[PDB]
Amino acid sequence: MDVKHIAKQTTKTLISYLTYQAVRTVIGQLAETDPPRSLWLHQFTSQESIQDGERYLEALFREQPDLGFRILTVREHLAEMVADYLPEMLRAGIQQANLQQRAQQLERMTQVSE
Amino acid sequence: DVKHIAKQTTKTLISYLTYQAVRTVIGQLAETDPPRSLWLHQFTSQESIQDGERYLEALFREQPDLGFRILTVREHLAEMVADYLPEMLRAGIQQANLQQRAQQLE
Image 1 (cartoon, rainbow over the protein chains, first blue to last red):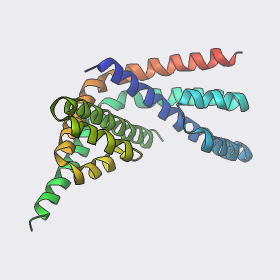
Image 2 (image 1 turned 90 degrees about the vertical axis):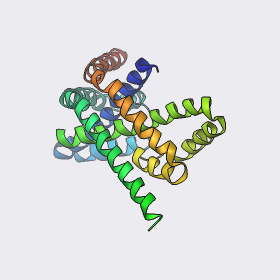
Image 3 (image 1 turned 180 degrees about the vertical axis):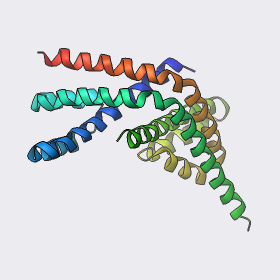
Image 4 (image 1 turned 135 degrees about the horizontal axis):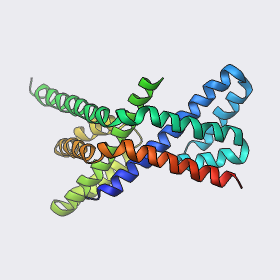
């Protein structure tokens, strides 16, 4: 199979997710220093969340570019903090989820005989 | 919180790889059992707006052999991708931020 395609697409998904986690973080920071801007950023994201992180940020920059810049910085820091954990967590997570899926289906199968 | 973040990130990745594994099995079925390939494509088109684990539970109710197959495939996809991610994510987020900043210098 095309591992390069899947690795790239996986990476794009990851960056989009961390972008949105960065948006949540800045919302929280604005709570400590400037509460009206927290609500604005939350509301903007409700109609603007349904898109790739890069398209969301371009939308944000048109309206509040100080916030767009803070998010670039936070998302880079979040990525630096999590990146090296991801391989083992993914492998362990998929092993655990697979076990649970199999055990549940087997329990279903033997329950349909009881 | 870094710990909550790396966990939630992981959940998101597992969901994504689950749906990638679905496409793999659709492709395999396109060879061995075209009507079931179509069936699985159609099911997935209606059941994908949920976490991968809930998708699998639903699939297991209908076509359990396909659920079992997707579990094995997603494990393989994880193994094929996982060790690229620390580099791809760092390099990717650096280039994406460079692009954003170059754009907004306009």
